[PDB]
Image (cartoon, rainbow, N blue to C red; front, side):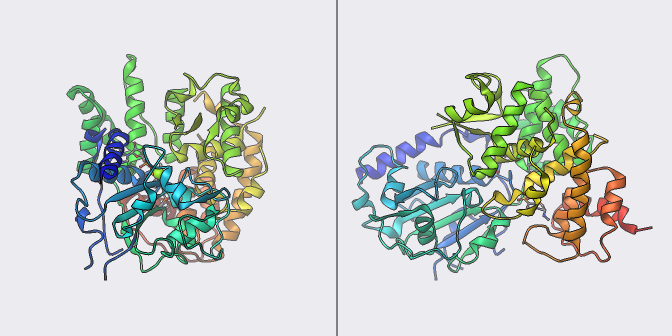
Length: 471
Ligand SMILES: CN[C@@H]1COc2c(S(=O)(=O)NC(=O)Nc3c4c(cc5c3CCC5)CCC4)cnn2C1
Ligand SMILES: Nc1ncnc2c1ncn2[C@@H]1O[C@H](COP(=O)(O)OP(=O)(O)O)[C@@H](O)[C@H]1O
Ligand SMILES: [Mg+2]
């Protein structure tokens, strides 16, 4: 078992940072709890899927579980190997074997894979970010592989592993956004489903106090945040807390008095961009658009140079908080920022037509284009800064009109998880505060049905309904 201890030590080394102290627990609701009882029966479950909103903390949950297992505190008598598969890195088109996939996660270049697969009952895989798989993923592609040694396409390998036909006795855990279940239904095998909820108000304050190392700064920041309620109730998503606290730190550097007027998600992201920030921006948005359309999330130095980085602007300027270097490869800190920049790509004047963008919306192959549409809804409103002089004005009109038409076609129907749901058609309107546009769009709802499960849910529904009287 010497290699077992070596792998545990290497994993401890990798997942030590994010640090452990920074972790703030999030809620969970099984049956959709005890973290050590997830894989026990109440026969035994072999697949458990964690569903949650983007930015809710799926990846950090996976990394914390990794660290806990490495420390020997969690599943200490259940699993012997805990292989972290980052779905962002895995490529569907490329031909690879499961042995090579396992080797890609090990410390040394000579893993006893043959020894490892002797006891598959003590092996668990962590497919973190299923919606992040790039390219087209056929639901019924085959034939499904059987043995790890053999090499097949990424699609076949991933699907066969998911269908519990490759290493049948191995345990699996996939962390997916709920939008992607439409394609994950056909593959799952008697799955268990768990949900990540968000940050409670008490845990919101806890995070705000752990962010800072001095009492005065944390107290002032919390006081400023609480005094406005929309941002505070939208702060149950940890990524919003991260953005707001990082911006607060940036403002606190200088003597300027703190301030946060952000009312919507688009406003939050725009405030972040302004706080942390021409030739620099157009390439920054072209990179995001190309990555979204061409199914590229990680970009090589050559790719960065192609768009306009000009051998610079990323060593210091953009990497400050936007980009992140991984393993030559520079990605975006969070996919939401990439989608924000892709949406901005449609609203810069020196810009592909939005009609083709909307035509393929909610598709798994194209990345579901969800945050892109929401962010271009938010960014186009005329009511909403040095940046507003940059985004194109005339084109807005055209896209505005097209958006309206989209609404007209998407309300004469019903949908629950196929993506343009009534609630999601409303979230998009909420991002566009303009009263006139919201009224005209709401004019296309002869009947309304909505399922409400959070407080932001209730706020958005109430805002849409208030203008929905139809006069
Ligand atoms: C009725 N559909 C609503 C559609 O959305 C959403 C998701 S998600 O996968 O779309 N994720 C998000 O929408 N995340 C999100 C983010 C920010 C701010 C807000 C949300 C949702 C509440 C407000 C900033 C970072 C990501 C999950 N449930 N719902 C609710
Ligand atoms: N427990 C936590 N403590 C501190 N920050 C968190 C926590 N959970 C999530 N976050 C923040 O929320 C953001 C969500 O990103 P991440 O969880 O890595 O990916 P995903 O959005 O797929 O879950 C992160 O940038 C992180 O800073
Ligand atoms: Mg993630």
